[PDB]
Length: 111
Length: 100
Image (tube, rainbow over all chains, first blue to last red; front, side, top):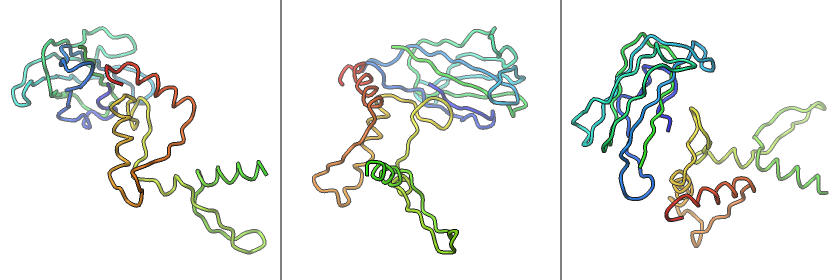
């Protein structure tokens, strides 16, 4: 449930969040966790950038999910993770920051 | 003799090709191990960057990849040598699936 580790510029422009889990019933829960680090990858710290996520049921029509600011990201988070109910096959992520930070992105899905 | 055979086994698995001049001035060679030649299908299972998340689907893909080329293998048969912990973990993972 980890999408990408490392450079913000290296965040994929499109992410496949369609998952075959449990039975043939599609998943109906989507939650995103974002964790920022310091200059060193291991030690955690804050960040300046802001992340925005969009989801598409058909891959071309996007629906707003939420936004996360790396300023609140740290050892103890203060923001609220984005939450969406419905069917999503693709995830669109856009960053607005200086870049060159090691970041964590996690996607959690539920039946 | 047991030590000899254990050393031969470990060399065949983890050896690497080399050729170097020995102390007496004569060549010294080391054989290339099994893992030296297998490069197409090498997978590191785990969490983090550079590793593959361990699930049933990943295991099925890993095991079905080797059957892509029949090659010289007759009857479509393969031999698997696995550790006890890995086999037990596979047995545990097969339980959660609605169909094993």
